[PDB]
Structures are given as structure tokens and as C-alpha cells.
Amino acid sequence: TPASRYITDMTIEELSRDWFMLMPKQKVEGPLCIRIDQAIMDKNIMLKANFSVIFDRLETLILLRAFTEEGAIVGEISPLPSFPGHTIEDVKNAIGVLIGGLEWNDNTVRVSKTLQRFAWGS
Amino acid sequence: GSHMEMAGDLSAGFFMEELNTYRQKQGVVLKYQELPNSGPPHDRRFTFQVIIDGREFPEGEGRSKKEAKNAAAKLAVEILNKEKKAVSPLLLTTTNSSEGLSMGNYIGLINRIAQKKRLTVNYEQCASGVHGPEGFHYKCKMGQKEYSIGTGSTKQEAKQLAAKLAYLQILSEETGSGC
């Protein structure tokens, strides 16, 4: 799990931020996590994780959270596990569905970053 | 006008079956539109109208043979390429133009909104603990005539009210000219 093939985005502070749900909104198709709060909608979510790579491709994921400059949160996003864990090609859908939630109200959605580069592809 | 001029399958459609490619994303299941050999000044060019977006006249044509209908979808390559330029004004005129959950803090953008005259915005207290809440009358400012002021019992329950009243001063203050 070298740093050349394992990257620690989230520091020791991005791990345990909690916030509270006015009216959340959830959806999922496969191994990704999705959320928008509908009263607290369109806040900055900073989804960082300690991921890994191999051959410029998939090794793993941990979790993702929400952060702004002010520090608020609209919801939560992460690479979800499943029966096989996190299917790469299903991340095409799980991250796939994870891209278009809030987009109806002209405010773009947040997506998970781990399964993007190596699961959401292939 | 003409992309190909000689093509043609011999067991398939061609201008519908071999014509399947670009209309995957351009998205047109043509209940087909036919403008073949429409030239008024003596031109029989097959504009067997393939479509770019759902009604349009993709068209480029040269003769009533393999020449013509191919460059029908000539511009049905393009109007997706063309027109990628903007459509909206400064924002979408949509009834849902950007959300974003505007700031809940007060003294944050107060100094911004102190742009009324670029004010001295300042806050201080002497928080008694004698009896513990013994008395906290607050004295600060935004604006320059309504000295932002608060009053309360316990500290954090009353820490802002002047500074709240500060941040909520200038937008009501007629000041900025001196009186």
C-alpha cells in the first residue's frame, strides 16, 4: 500500500464531522453513498478518503464526508459497500446515480471520489 | 452537401440501419421525414431527411443517387457541435437558480457590509461572574448613529445582541453622509 499507490486525502481531522438533517434526500444504485438535505441543500461537501491505486487503477476506498469554507454540510457521500463490497462497474451507477441528485434545482450534486477514478471507470 | 457519394450496403438498411450511429446521443427515432429530390430549379437530390434534434432538416445533397442523402446528417453532426455556446443570462431564468444556504454568521460579512462607509467594527466585553450572570449590557457598533447595544443575563446567551445589532445596523442606517 505505497503512497505511490495509496493516497491519504483525508487527514486526521476530516474523519469525524457530524451535522444534522433538516430534510435529507437519498438515492443509490450500487456501491456508493449519496445524500442531500432538502432544507440544507447545496452546501460544500469535501469528500476526502485514504484511497489506494495499482497500475494507475483500483485498489480501495475508506469513506467520505462533507466540508465547506464556512464548514457547513448539505449531506453525506461515500463509496458504499455491497455483497461483493464495491463493484467497480456498479460504481458507474453508484457514482453514476451519485452525480445527478440536486441537479434539478440548478445546484450540482456531490459524488464520491474513491470509486470514481478506478471503479466509476470500468 | 456530400459526405459520401457512392456508399450502400447490400443486406441491411443503409440510411436507417447503417444510419444508427450519431442518433444514439442526438436521440432521434425518426418516424422518417422524407424530402427526396426537392430541388425546384431542376435538381433531383435525395434529401431523405435525417434529423439532428427532432424536426430539423439535416440536409446536404448532390444527386438522385448515392450522392445525396448522406450529407443530410452533415449538419446533424454539427448542431450538437455548434450551439454549445451559452443560452442563459447571468443566471438561469429557471425558478430554481442557484441555492447555497446563505451565511448564518453576523460579524463575518459585517465588515463587508461595513462598506456603507468602511466602518470601524469592534466588540469587547467585561463578562462579570460576580453572581455569575450579574449583568451584561452590551455596547458596540456598526453604523455611526445607532450604537449597537445589547443586554442580557448570561454571557453566550447575550454575547451577540449588540454585535448582532451591529451587523443588523447599517442596512437600516441612513448614515454614510454624517448625520
Image (cartoon, grey):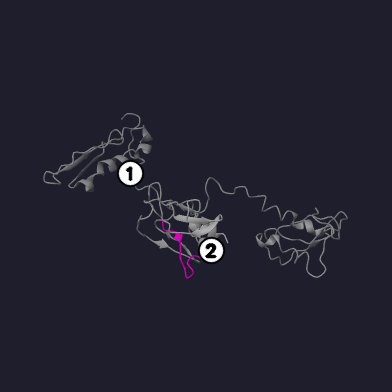
Q: Does A74 sit above or below residue B12?
A: above
Q: Position of residue B156 (x, y in %)?
A: 23, 47
Any part of residue A100 in sight: no
| Secondary structure under the numbered disc 2 in the rendered image | helix
Q: Residues within 10 Å of mark 2 (few under 14, many from 20)?
A: many
Q: Nearer the viewer, residue A14 or A45?
A: A14
Please report, as a chain letter, where disc 1 is located: B
Boundaries of the magenta span: A74-91
Location of residue A65 in the rendering, given as x and y in whole percent from the top left corner = 41, 56
Q: Which residue is mark 2?
A: A88
Subunit bearing disc 2? A
Q: Tell whether B140 sits left or right of A112.
A: left
State the predominant SS element of the stretch in magenta.
loop
Quadrant of the image containing the C terminus of chain B? top left
Tag 1: residue type? Tyr
Q: Quadrant of residue B124?
A: top left
Q: Quick one: which residue is furthest to the top in this view?
A: B178
In the rendered view, tell whether residue A25 sits above or below residue B149: below
Q: Is residue B140 a member of the stretch shown in magenta?
A: no
Task: Give the residue drawn at x 52%, y 48%.
Answer: B91
Which of the two discs, 2 and 1, sits closer to the camera?
Answer: 2
The answer to which image quadrant residue A78 occupies is: bottom left
Q: Residues within 10 Å of mark 1 (few under 14, many from 20)?
A: some
B23 left or right of B68 in image: left
Residue beneath disc 1: B106
Q: CA distance from mark 2 to mark 1?
A: 45 Å
What percent of the width, then of the height, locates residue B146? Answer: 27, 36
